[PDB]
Every structure is written in C-alpha cells, then in structure tokens.
Image 1 (cartoon, rainbow, N blue to C red):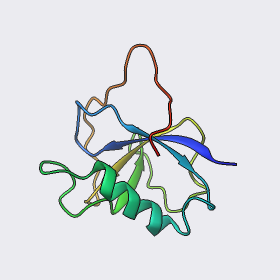
Image 2: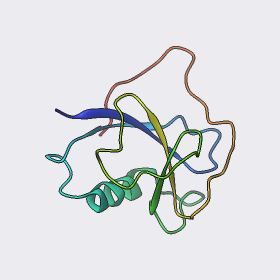
Image 3: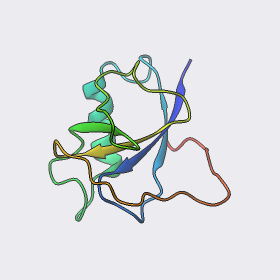
Image 4: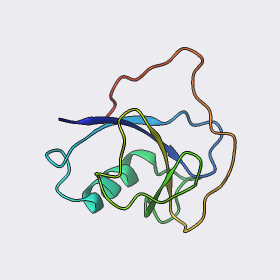
Length: 100
C-alpha cells in the first residue's frame, strides 16, 4: 500500500532526489514525513529551516496531505513559501530504488 515518490530540494540543480515509500503506516502524520525529509534532505547549504513545504515538480501547487501524493511523481521540498524554478535533474537511465 506504500507509494514510491521522489523528493528534491528547492533550488538544487545537482541533487537528483531521494525515493521514499510513503503510506500512513510508515508515517503517523504529514508532519512526521516532513520531519523525516528534514533529516534526509537538509545539509549545510540546503534547507535552512528544514522541510516546511512540499511543491509539485512544476511548482504549480503545494501538497498538504499524504493523499495528495501520486505514485512515481517528483516533488520539491522547501524551507520557504516560494518555489525556485531551477532546472531539476534526473539520471538518463532511471533508478527508482527506494532509499526511504
């Protein structure tokens, strides 16, 4: 019942995302997911206040619940209430292995 979703960091052109297996069984709440994403995506140059917002890869909308997440889709994690429309990148030959 878990959904394979790719997460990127806002404004990072070099980072190719991390694959998560998402379900309400793995994460108690959406905050619990944002807490886990803060640990795995945050670093010295990225995410100053950790993961506080999730955007669709085109930055058209913000994701507020686990249900809003679609299987195999890519999302952008941010510390700020704005989307950095940078050229996000993927491998030419995929790797959809969970990192979770």
